[PDB]
Length: 9
Length: 10
Length: 233
Length: 238
Ligand SMILES: COC(=O)CC1CCC(=C(c2ccc(O)cc2)c2ccc(O)cc2)CC1
Ligand SMILES: COC(=O)CC1CCC(=C(c2ccc(O)cc2)c2ccc(O)cc2)CC1
Image (cartoon, rainbow over all chains, first blue to last red; front, side):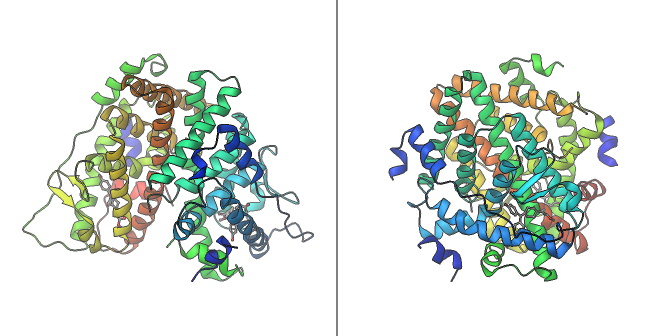
């Protein structure tokens, strides 16, 4: 989940 | 044409 | 155009009096639970509802002023949205249920018959629950449904936008009478119109699923419904 | 929450400061356009825009208060909507043209490269012309864009996280009205303009859905390399 990673930081 | 045509003017 | 001379109350009474009746589904079966049976009942119901919608649209203030071809475009563009907001409206006093007809009350479990129906059902139920918590009134509902009719196909026009502003004035007038403050008025107005974005979404998603039904040739839909379908492609 | 305690002006400046940059596209005016290159440029562009949108969404008031899983859902739901309203905003002062990038200015004739694209392009053009006639303000645009982010996926989630989102949405509605009141609009004009703006969102949703199903079709038609992030955004709509 790329979107999930980029949202964390 | 369309059935909708007929129903709009009846 | 006569529609612009109308007062807020004249606008409300005109819309309320133009309301289509609540049709019944085909009585009896086995309480659906098959793909062809359920889609058959829904298609039959929708086809009969379309006839009333067309006559309802002609009574919506300003719709008669449009070109016949423009009338065709707006209806072809918004017919499933109008059906859905009606279904959602009827399903208000029935939490967790979708009142397609008084003798056809469905829940999400009964949507497992058709692929992708549970998803749409959940969105419809969510909209109905949203209407309920907002305590949507009938006077507000008929304004929203008329807005959908005139707005959904306008970008695909000065008169329509003038009529749209007129309905906006009517909505505000309805809320002002309900004792809502100036802040509560524009907030509720926004809340109602944002739901229309979701009704659009459900219609788009719901439309696609009607395509795959037509290609599968599972249910004999009418030529009218087929022409309303072809227009979205 | 801090978003609920933000004044109207504080809300505007916050959204304005959080604005993502206008990215350039890889585009060679010398190179011949094909129905795989031009889609490739838009795909390459949108993919880079997504990275800025994600960080932009973080700075949208109330968005960080939400669960990470709901942040994913909202963005998966409205990413093409936000891209499109951005595109439409940039293309306002270019009648009959879509400014995908400062170096990528397209009209309907060049949209014929791809099938079904010209219908999307005309709808985008109409939305842009609509914004132009309304004389949409930047302060209003950033409000609308933030509304899309929070609203588009709120009915597809006893979490009670929905209540906070609606509370923020109401605050943004208060912001819009405050803007129109400062522009010298009468009370009737305020409610009308507000309604006019939000009805456009219904059309932007329509364009997104139609655009989405056209992105999903050419995904199966391997003619265009969709980026890994973009593919995961497409999977969300199924
Ligand atoms: C995949 O399954 C789904 O998407 C379910 C969805 C439910 C709603 C809908 C329909 C519908 C169903 C079949 C049609 O041919 C025409 C209209 C509908 C019917 C009556 C009504 O008052 C409002 C809408 C469309 C289908
Ligand atoms: C098939 O023809 C079409 O429908 C054209 C449509 C045009 C707009 C759009 C895109 C788009 C195009 C390709 C993608 O992979 C991702 C995003 C877009 C790109 C950037 C931007 O800032 C805003 C939007 C989607 C495509």
